[PDB]
Amino acid sequence: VSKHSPLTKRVLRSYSNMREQTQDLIDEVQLERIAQLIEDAERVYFFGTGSSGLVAREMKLRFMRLGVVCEALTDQDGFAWTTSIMDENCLVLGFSLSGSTPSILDSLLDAKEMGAKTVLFSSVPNKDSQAYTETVLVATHSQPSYIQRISAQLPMLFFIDLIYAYFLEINRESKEKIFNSYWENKKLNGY
Amino acid sequence: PDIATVIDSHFEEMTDLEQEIARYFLQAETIQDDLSSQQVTQKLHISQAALTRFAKKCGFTGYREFIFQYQHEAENQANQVSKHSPLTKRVLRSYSNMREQTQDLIDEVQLERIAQLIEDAERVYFFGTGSSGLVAREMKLRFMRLGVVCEALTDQDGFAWTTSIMDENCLVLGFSLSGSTPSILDSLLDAKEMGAKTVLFSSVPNKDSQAYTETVLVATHSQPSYIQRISAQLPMLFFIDLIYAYFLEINRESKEKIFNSYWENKKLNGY
Amino acid sequence: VSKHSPLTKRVLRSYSNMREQTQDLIDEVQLERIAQLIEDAERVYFFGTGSSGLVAREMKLRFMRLGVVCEALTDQDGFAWTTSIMDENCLVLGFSLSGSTPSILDSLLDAKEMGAKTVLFSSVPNKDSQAYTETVLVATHSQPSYIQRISAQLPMLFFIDLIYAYFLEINRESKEKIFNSYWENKKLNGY
Amino acid sequence: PDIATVIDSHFEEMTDLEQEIARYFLQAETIQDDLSSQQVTQKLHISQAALTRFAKKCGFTGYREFIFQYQHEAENQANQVSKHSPLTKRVLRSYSNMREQTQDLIDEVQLERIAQLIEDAERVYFFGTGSSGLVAREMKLRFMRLGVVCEALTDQDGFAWTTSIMDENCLVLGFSLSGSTPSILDSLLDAKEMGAKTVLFSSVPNKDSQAYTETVLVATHSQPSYIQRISAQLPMLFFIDLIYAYFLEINRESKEKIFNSYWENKKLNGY
Ligand SMILES: CC(=O)N[C@H]1[C@@H](O)[C@H](O)[C@@H](COP(=O)(O)O)O[C@@H]1O
Ligand SMILES: CC(=O)N[C@H]1[C@@H](O)[C@H](O)[C@@H](COP(=O)(O)O)O[C@@H]1O
Ligand SMILES: CC(=O)N[C@H]1[C@@H](O)[C@H](O)[C@@H](COP(=O)(O)O)O[C@@H]1O
Ligand SMILES: CC(=O)N[C@H]1[C@@H](O)[C@H](O)[C@@H](COP(=O)(O)O)O[C@@H]1O
Ligand SMILES: [Cl-]
Ligand SMILES: [Cl-]
Ligand code: NA
Ligand code: NA
Ligand code: NA
Ligand code: NA
C-alpha cells in the first residue's frame, strides 16, 4: 500500500543485492586478464545449458561484433564435436551457475586435454575448478527457493559486461570499426 | 587514531573508577558483550552518568558517540573505491541506474493485469530478435515450468506462420527494445487482427503502442553509445522477473507442483 | 571414366536403395492412422537429437503451416519440461534412428505416463517399442560405416512426407487456406 | 499355372527317361541345387538334348526357358501396386524423380572443386533460411566431425555480423532453393566484397550467380504446387552428400581420426 507492493519489492531487492554482492566479488586483475585471453585466442567458445546457455548465446553475439571469431554451443554433442577440433589457440568459457552440470564440467577438461585454455563461471566454488585456467565466481541468488528466484542469467551477465568493457578497450579502434560496419552504407546486409 | 590508543592515552587522566571502566572497554572481548548503555551500566555496577563522564574524558560528546566509534571500528576496513578501475565503476553504475530507472516505470496494476492475461490465455507466444530473442526464450523456459503452454520465436518466417494459427485465446508478448523492429511490430498487428491479445515491451514510447492490448515501457540504457551499452536484455529481464512474480502467485499450489515435477523421482527425464 | 565417378555412383546408389527399401516397409494403414492422430490431437510434439533433431525441426515447420499447433524440442531439459505439461490430448513423435538415444526413449515413456499418445521412428526394432502407441520402422542406411553414410535424416524424411500427404487430404480445404495465408495480401508479415 | 502341375500334367506324355527327369524337378528341394544345364545334366547322368526334349514336352521352347520360369516362381509373389494408394505413389515418384533430376545436373569437377575449396579454407560458413536453414545446419554438423572449422547461420543479423569478420580465407556456402531470398543473396555479395569465396545452391539459374565463385544448380521439385511439394531440403541434401563424399577422401586418415574421436575412450564427453 506504499510506493510498491511486497512482491515488486522482493524482485527489485534481489536485483540490488545481486549488484552489491557482485561488487564485493570482482577480481579486476582476473577479469582484465581474461579479457586479454579472448584477444590472444584464435577461436573462442561459449558452453552453457538452459539459462546459462542463453548467457553464452548473448556473449557470442556481443563479442562477434567486436571482431572475435567465436561460437556458442548448448548441447552435449556440440561440446564433444567442438572439443575434438580444439587446440592451444582455443579458449573456452564454461557457464554453469550450479558448478555441477556434468556436460559443462567434462567439456572444460576435454578442452584442457586438447590444450585449450579454460574459464569457468559458477556461483559455487569447487575443487575441479583448480584444473581450469581461470574460475570466475559469480554472485548467488538471494532467494532460498529456486522457483522464486530472479533470472538465472544475471550473476553471469554482470561479469560478461565487465569483461566486455575491459576487452573493448584493447585495440578499441579496430573493434569499434568492426562494430560500426553493421550500419555502414556499403554493407549490403546492414541496418 | 585507534580507539584503543585513545583510552590508553587518557587512562592517566581518569578517576579511580573511570580507569576501571577503561579496562572493560580495553579488553578486546567486550566488543562481543551487550553495550546498550544499560547492560554495560549493570555489568560494571555503575551509573549511566559515570559512563558519560568516561566518554567525555576520552574526547567524545557522550557515551553514545564513543560506543558508536568503538564498535564500528570492527568493520571499518576500506571504504574507498576498492573497485578502483573507473571502467568497472562505469558498468556497475549502468546496472544500478537501470534498476533505479525500472522502479520509476513500474505500473503495478498493468504488470499484474498482464500476469492475469497469461493465465487466462490458452497459448502464449514470445516474439523477439537478437538480444530481444534471448529474452523471449528465457521467458518461455521460465513460464513453461509453471505449466504455461508457450513457444518462443525469433525469425520473421516463424512469426508469420505462428500468427496464422492464432485466435482470440492466444496472447503474444513482443520484445523490441528500440520499438522499431518491423517484424516484431508487424507481427503484433498480425496477431491482433486474428483476435489475439498483444503486449509490447519497448523503451521508446511509440504511437503504434495504442494498437496493442498492453504496452510496457522498460528502461533506457545509461550509455549514449551502443557499443559501450551493457547487455540489451536487462531492461526486459527486470519486467519479466516482475511479471513472473505476480504470475507465480496465481494458483501457486498448481504451478509449484508442475515446477517441482522436474525433480520428481517418478519423472523419467528429470534431475 | 564414364557418366559418373565411382564416388558419385556410391552416393546416388545409397539414395536409390533408400527408396527401394522404404517402399517395402510402408504400412499404409499405419501411416494414415498416424496422420489422423495428428489431426485429433490438441498439441503435437517432435523430439529428436542431432540429425534426427533437424528432422523434427522441419516437420514442425511443415505441419504448423497446415494449422497444427506443434513444437519441436531437441534437448533433454526441453523434453522433461514439455512432458511435465502433457495430457491425453497430446501426441509425441520421437525420432531416433538408432532406436537407442536414452533421452528420446525416456521421453516417450514420460509422455506415455502423462497420457499422451506416442509414436517412435527408428531403423532398429526393439522391445520397448511395444509400449508406444505406434512404431514406424524406417529404412537402414546401406553404407556399413557411419562416416561414409548419406544424410541421417533421409530414412525419416521419407515417412514424414508420406504422413504429410495423408494428413494434408484430411479437411484439406481448411489446411490449404491456413497455408496460403502466408502469401495473403492482408497478412502484415507475409511474403 | 503352377510349374509343378504342368510337369504333372505332362508326366504321362513323357518317355521313360523324361519321366525320371520330371521326378528330379518335381522334388521341392532341387530348387536349391545348381541348374546351369551342365550340373543338372551331370547329376542325372543325361545329355543336354535329353533335358531340352523334356522342356518342349512340358510346353517350353527349350530347357533355358523352363528353368527360368521354374526358378523365378520362388520369388514371384506380388508384382502389382502393393503400395496401392496413389498418394503414396505420388511421394515415391517425387523422390525418384529428384534423384534422376540430380544425376543429370552433376558437374563432377565443380563438386570436387568445391570439396577442395572447403579444405583450403580456414573458416567455412553455411547460410540458409527456413528449410534451407536445416540443410545448412546439417552440413555444419557433418563437416565439423571431419575437423572443419565451420558455423551455420539462419537469420539476417547473423549473416551481417558474420560477413563483417570474413576475409579471403573464408568460404561461404549459401542455400536458397528459390534463388531469390534477399538475405542469402545479399550476404554472398557481402562476403565476396570481404574477399571470401562464395558458393550458391539454388534450383533456379539466376544471373546474380555470375557474382559467386561457384553456383550449384540443384533439382526442382516435381510437384507444381508448393503445398504438395515434398521436403524442401532434398534438392540440396543430394549435393551435400556428394560434396561430403568428395571432401571425405581428401586427407581421409586425418578426418576419420577426428570423426572417430567422438567414440574415443579417452574422450570425456563422447558416447
Ligand atoms: C536448478 C535448475 O532448475 N536448473 C535448470 C536451469 O535453471 C539451469 O540454467 C540449467 C543449467 O544449469 P547451470 O549449468 O548450473 O547454470 O540446468 C537446469 O535446466
Ligand atoms: C541497435 C542494434 O544493434 N540492434 C541489434 C541488436 O542489438 C538488437 O538486439 C536486435 C533487436 O532490436 P530490438 O527489437 O530493438 O530489441 O536488432 C539487432 O540485432
Ligand atoms: C552414430 C552417430 O554418429 N550419432 C549422432 C547423430 O548421427 C545422430 O543423429 C544423433 C541422434 O541419434 P538418433 O537418436 O539415433 O537418431 O546422435 C549422434 O549425435
Ligand atoms: C516458398 C516458401 O514457402 N519459402 C519458405 C520456406 O519454404 C523456405 O524454405 C524459406 C527459404 O527459401 P529458399 O531460400 O528459396 O530455400 O523461405 C520461406 O520460409
Ligand atoms: Cl542498486
Ligand atoms: Cl530411384
Ligand atoms: Na533472487
Ligand atoms: Na548502459
Ligand atoms: Na548410406
Ligand atoms: Na515434389
Image (cartoon, coloured by chain):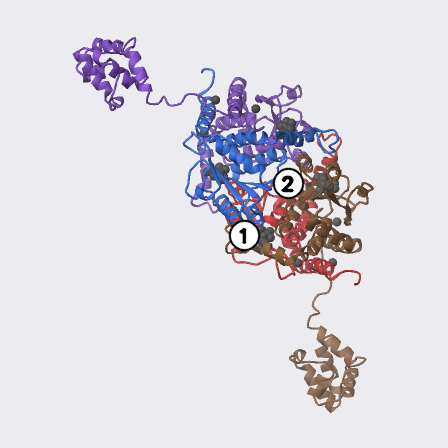
Chain colours: A blue, B purple, C red, D brown
Between A76 and D177, the one lying in front of the other is: A76
In the rendered image, residue C40, in percent from the top left (x then y), is placed at 61, 43
Q: Is residue A45 in sight in this rendering? A: yes
Between D14 and D154, the one lying in front of the other is: D154
- Splitting the image into 4 quarters, where does residue B19 fall? top left
Asked whether, in this view, residue B164 is left or right of residue B119, the answer is: right
Query: As displayed, is residue D135 above or below residue D47?
Result: above
Between C50 and D213, the one lying in front of the other is: D213
Q: Going by the picture, which residue comes out furthest to the bottom?
A: D16
Q: Is residue A152 in sight in this rendering? A: no
In the rendered image, residue B50, in percent from the top left (x then y), is placed at 21, 10
Label 1: how many Cα within 10 Å (few below 14, some 14–19, many 20+): few
- CA distance separating discs 2 and 1: 27 Å
Q: Residue C68 carries which label?
A: 2
Q: What residue type is labelled 1?
A: Thr
Mark 1 belongs to which subunit?
Answer: C
**Mark 2 sits near ligand 4, with its Cβ under 8 Å away:** no
Mark 2 belongs to which subunit?
Answer: C
Query: As displayed, is residue D64 above or below residue A22?
Result: below
- Dot 2 or dot 1, earlier in sequence: 2
Count of marks, rendered view: 2
- Residue depicted at 71% across the width and 87% down the height: D42
Disc 1 designates what residue? Answer: C101
In the rendered image, residue B114, in percent from the top left (x then y), is placed at 55, 25
Helix, strand or loop under label 1: loop
Q: Check chain identity for marks 2 and 1: say if they share one.
A: yes
**Mark 1 sits near ligand 3, with its Cβ under 8 Å away:** yes
Q: What residue type is labelled 2?
A: Val
